[PDB]
Image: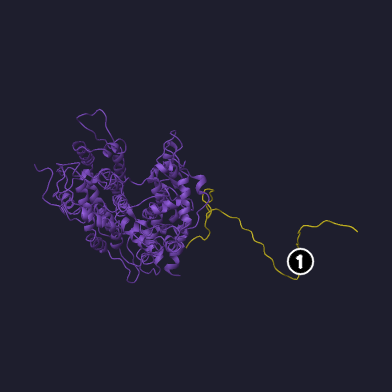
C-alpha cells in the first residue's frame, strides 16, 4: 500500500529528453455569454478625401 | 487486487527513486577519473555507500514476493534481479571477512613489487617500463624471467588466500538455491516462462562443446602458422613436432597476440595500411574524428542524439597540472546524460575504437524509456559487444574512399587482404580456445571435483590439450598461475569474451544480407543502407526486457550460435593457410617438454 505522489529531480546537465518543459494550454468554448477577448492584427494608415 | 497489481506499484516506486541515486554518485564518479583530488576521494566514501545502502533496503522488503503466481514475463526478470542478494546472505563476521579481502586483491595487482635479486638497484611495475621491455624481447633468458617472476612472487601469498576464497564463495550459491559460484555468472542467462524457447541449466556445457569441435580446425591452421614463421627467429627452442612455450606470445598471459605480429607478417614488401600519416598532413584535431563518425550514423538510419554532448564533455587532456585516468571506459550516468572520457592522439587505432565507443552511446539512447534494472544489454555481455561490429565496417578500405582518409587511387590485390584478415584474427579469433581454457578451469574447481594436490595437476595437462601449450618451467604447489590476471582478483566476468566473436560475426551475416553486399564479409559496409538500419533499430530498443533467445530470431532467424558465418570470414584465408602448412607437421605432441634435458 503505497503513497501515490512521486518526486521530481531537477539538474541542468541532463539533456533534451530529461529537461523540464513548462506547458500551459488555452481552452476555448462556446456558451450563452458573448465573445469577450478579441484580436489585434496590425492596422493600416488612415487616409482622407 | 492480485499480486500482479501489487508488483507494479512497488517497482514503479523503485524506478524514479533509482534514477536520482544512480545519477548523484556517478556525477562525482565521472569527476573521479577526470580529477584525482583529496576532495573527491572522500566523496567516494560519501556517495559510494549510498548505492550500497539502497540496494539492501529494497531487498529488505521484496524477498517475500513469490515468483510462482506471476503471469507476465517482464516482472519476473525484474524481480529475480531484485531478489538475488549477493554477498548479504552470510552472517556478520563472514561478510566482513569478504569485504576486507577484496580490498587486498585490487591493491596487490597494480602496486605489486617484484624485481631482480642479481641487480636490485632499480625495479619495475606492471604499467610502466614493463610494457616497453616486453614489446622488444627477441632474446630468450631476458623474457623467461619476466613471465616467471610475475607468477611466482605475486601468487605466493595469494595461494593460501585463495584457499579461503574457494570455500567462502560456495556459500553464495547454496543460500541462493544454486550449486556453485561458477554458475553465478550464467544465472543471468536463464529464460523461463516461454514455450519451446526455454533455456536449461545444463545447456552451456552442451552448446559450447558442440561449437568447440567445429572451431578445432580453425585454431589448428592458425597454430601451425605461428610455428612456421618463428623458425628463423628461434632455431633451437621451438620444436616442430612439440608445443609452444607460453611467454613467446607477446603478452603477460597470451590473451593478446597483437605484439608477436612484428615477426609473423606474411609480406614485408607490401606495407600495412595506416591512416596515421595521412591525417597529420591534412591538419586534423581530436574533435573532427567524432565529427566524421557522427555522419556515419545518419546514413544508416539512426537518429541524431542530444545537443548537450559536445559542450559539457572533454576529449583532449588539459595539461599536466592535474591527474586524470584516461582509460577508455564507457559511461552511463542515467537520466539522458551520456558522457565519455578517453585518451586521445592521432593514431590509426583511435579511429578504430571511435566507432566502438560511439557504438556504446548510440545503443544507450534507445532503451532510456525502459525501467532501470532492465536497462542493460540483451545479455550482460551485449554492452561491450555492440561497438566492434560497426567498428569493423569502419576499418574497411571501401568506406575510407568515401570519407577520404585514403588516396583516391589505391590498388588492392590478393596479398593485401592477407594482412587485414590476420591482424583481426589476433585479438578476436585466436583467443577463443584461450578464453575456453581457464573457464573450464573455473567451473570444475567449484564443484568439488579435485583435491589440493590435483589443483595445479589439472592446469598444464589441459593447457597441452586445448591450446597446445607446454610450460617451460615446472611449477610447485606453492605457485598459482591464474592469480596474475586482471579478471580474476578484481571479480569481473571473463565469459563475455567467448561470445564476442559469436554474437558479432553472426549478426554481420544478417545485416550485410539486408544491405545487399556481394562478396566476402570483410568488404561489407553498413553505410548507405536504410534496409538493415530498421533491422538494427528493433534490436537497440529492447535490452533484456525482451529475452535474449527471442531476440536472436528477430535478426538472424536462428535460435543458437552458428560457426558457419565465421568460416565464411575465414574462407579466403582458408585457401592461403592450406598451401603454406603442407611442409609442416599438423597437430602437436603430448610428451614433448622444454625442461627435460
Q: Chain of mark 1?
A: A
Give left or right: position of B312 versus B38.
right
Q: Nearer the viewer, residue B193 or B223?
A: B223
Coordinates of residue B34 in the picture (x, y in percent): 44, 41
The residue that mark 1 highlights is A35
Give left or right: position of B335 versus B410.
right
Q: Is residue B180 visible?
A: no
Q: Which chain is yellow?
A: A
Coordinates of residue B75 in the picture (x, y in percent): 41, 64
User: Quick check: B1 above or below B301?
Assistant: below
Determine the residue positioned at 31% across, 39% down: B110
Q: Secondary structure at mark 1?
A: loop
Q: Residue furthest left?
A: B597
For disc 1, the neighbor class at 10 Å (few under 14, some 14 to 19, many from 20) is few
Q: Quadrant of the C terminus of chain B?
A: top left
Q: Which chain is purple?
A: B
Coordinates of residue B25 in the picture (x, y in percent): 44, 47
Q: Nearer the viewer, residue B238 or B123?
A: B238
Amino acid at each position: 500500500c503505497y503513497f501515490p505522489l512521486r518526486s521530481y529531480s531537477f539538474r541542468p546537465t541532463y539533456g533534451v529528453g530529461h529537461q523540464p518543459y513548462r506547458v500551459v494550454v488555452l481552452s476555448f468554448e462556446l456558451l450563452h455569454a458573448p465573445a469577450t477577448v478579441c484580436g489585434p492584427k496590425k492596422s493600416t494608415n488612415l487616409v482622407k478625401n | 487486487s492480485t499480486i500482479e497489481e501489487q508488483a507494479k506499484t512497488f517497482l514503479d516506486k523503485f524506478n524514479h527513486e533509482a534514477e536520482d541515486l544512480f545519477y548523484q554518485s556517478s556525477l562525482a564518479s565521472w569527476n573521479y577519473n577526470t580529477n584525482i583530488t583529496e576532495e573527491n576521494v572522500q566523496n567516494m566514501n560519501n556517495a559510494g555507500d549510498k548505492w550500497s545502502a539502497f540496494l539492501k533496503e529494497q531487498s529488505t522488503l521484496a524477498q517475500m514476493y513469490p515468483l510462482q503466481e506471476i503471469q507476465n514475463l517482464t516482472v519476473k526478470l525484474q524481480l529475480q534481479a531484485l531478489q538475488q542478494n549477493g554477498s548479504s546472505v552470510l552472517s556478520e563476521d563472514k561478510s566482513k571477512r569478504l569485504n576486507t579481502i577484496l580490498n587486498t586483491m585490487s591493491t596487490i595487482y597494480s602496486t605489486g613489487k617484484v624485481c631482480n635479486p642479481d641487480n636490485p638497484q632499480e625495479c619495475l611495475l606492471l604499467e610502466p617500463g614493463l610494457n616497453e621491455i616486453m614489446a622488444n624481447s627477441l632474446d630468450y633468458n631476458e623474457r623467461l624471467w619476466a613471465w616467471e617472476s610475475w607468477r611466482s612472487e605475486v601468487g605466493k601469498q595469494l595461494r593460501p588466500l585463495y584457499e579461503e576464497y574457494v570455500v567462502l564463495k560456495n556459500e553464495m550459491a547454496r543460500a541462493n538455491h544454486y550449486e556453485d559460484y561458477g554458475d553465478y555468472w550464467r544465472g543471468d542467462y536463464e529464460v523461463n516462462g516461454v514455450d519451446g524457447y526455454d533455456y536449461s541449466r545444463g545447456q552451456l556445457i552442451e552448446d559450447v562443446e558442440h561449437t568447440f569441435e567445429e572451431i578445432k580446425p580453425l585454431y589448428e591452421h592458425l597454430h601451425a602458422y605461428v610455428r612456421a614463421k618463428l623458425m628463423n627467429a628461434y632455431p633451437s627452442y621451438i620444436s616442430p613436432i612439440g608445443c609452444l612455450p607460453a611467454h613467446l606470445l607477446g603478452d603477460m598471459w597470451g590473451r593478446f597476440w597483437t605484439n608477436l605480429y612484428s615477426l609473423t607478417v606474411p609480406f614485408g614488401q607490401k606495407p600495412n595500411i595506416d591512416v596515421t600519416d595521412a591525417m597529420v598532413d591534412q591538419a586534423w584535431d581530436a574533435q573532427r574524428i567524432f565529427k566524421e563518425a557522427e555522419k556515419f550514423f545518419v546514413s544508416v538510419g539512426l537518429p541524431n542524439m542530444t545537443q548537450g554532448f559536445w559542450e559539457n564533455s572533454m576529449l583532449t587532456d588539459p595539461g599536466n597540472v592535474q591527474k586524470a585516468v584516461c582509460h577508455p571506459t564507457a559511461w552511463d550516468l542515467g537520466k539522458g546524460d551520456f558522457r565519455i572520457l578517453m585518451c586521445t592522439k592521432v593514431t590509426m587505432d583511435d579511429f578504430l575504437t571511435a566507432h566502438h565507443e560511439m557504438g556504446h552511446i548510440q545503443y544507450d539512447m534507445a532503451y532510456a524509456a525502459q525501467p532501470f534494472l532492465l536497462r542493460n544489454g540483451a545479455n550482460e555481455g551485449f554492452h561491450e559487444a555492440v561497438g566492434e561490429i560497426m567498428s569493423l565496417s569502419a576499418a574497411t578500405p571501401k568506406h575510407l574512399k568515401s570519407i577520404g582518409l585514403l588516396s583516391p587511387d589505391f590498388q588492392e590485390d590478393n596479398e593485401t587482404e592477407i594482412n587485414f584478415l590476420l591482424k583481426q584474427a589476433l585479438t578476436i579469433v585466436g583467443t577463443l580456445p584461450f578464453t575456453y581454457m581457464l573457464e573450464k578451469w573455473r567451473w570444475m574447481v567449484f564443484k568439488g571435483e579435485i583435491p589440493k594436490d590435483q589443483w595445479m595437476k589439472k592446469w598444464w595437462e589441459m593447457k597441452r590439450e586445448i591450446v597446445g601449450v607446454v610450460e617451460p618451467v615446472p611449477h610447485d604447489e606453492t605457485y598459482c598461475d591464474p592469480a596474475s590476471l586482471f579478471h580474476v582478483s578484481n571479480d569481473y566476468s571473463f565469459i563475455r569474451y567467448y561470445t564476442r566473436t559469436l554474437y558479432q560475426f553472426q549478426f554481420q551475416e544478417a545485416l550485410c544480407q539486408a544491405a545487399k553486399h556481394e562478396g566476402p564479409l570483410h568488404k561489407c559496409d553498413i553505410s548507405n543502407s536504410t534496409e538493415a538500419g530498421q533491422k538494427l533499430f528493433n534490436m537497440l530498443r529492447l535490452g533484456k526486457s525482451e529475452p535474449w533467445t527471442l531476440a536472436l530470431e528477430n535478426v538472424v532467424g536462428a535460435k543458437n550460435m552458428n560457426v558457419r558465418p565465421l568460416l565464411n570470414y575465414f574462407e579466403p584465408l582458408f585457401t592461403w593457410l592450406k598451401d603454406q602448412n603442407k611442409n609442416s607437421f599438423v597437430g602437436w605432441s603430448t610428451d614433448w617438454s622444454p625442461y627435460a634435458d
